[PDB]
Image (cartoon, rainbow, N blue to C red; front, side, top):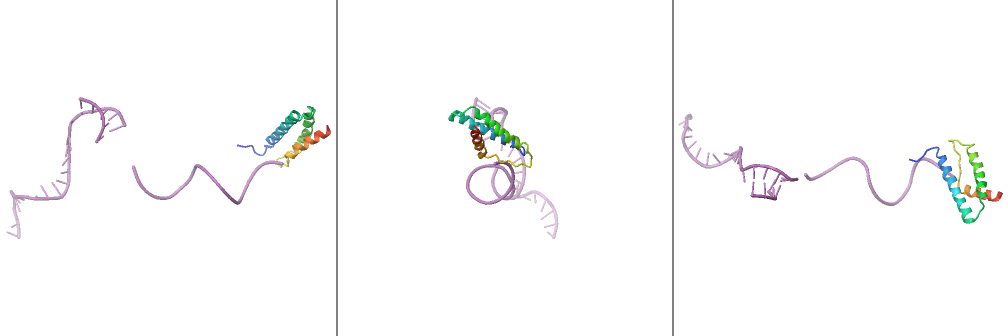
Length: 79
RNA sequence: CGCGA
DNA sequence: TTGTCTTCAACTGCTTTCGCGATGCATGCATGCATGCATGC
């Protein structure tokens, strides 16, 4: 039934999806700027590209909820 | 062994 | 000693025409709750 060994993709897709879900709720409900999004695509882009420049079935991934919040804060603070 | 002459 | 018709008595066959109409016992999957094992971060 469920994917094997390269559900790394679905993992990063529920993760990415859940993040964008949170941004929808913070521009909408917390009256953030539209710019935040592009700031966030950049930071999560940077680290997505870094885990996909260390991507291997010998996998060492640690995307936690803490990572979501961490890139929101990270991006907010640049802004 | 139940239904019809 | 012996012949056999004598007698009672153990087996054994059928019955007016058509339509409407298996039991028990072992094996294992099923259900549910609680420990363990595998995936991921």
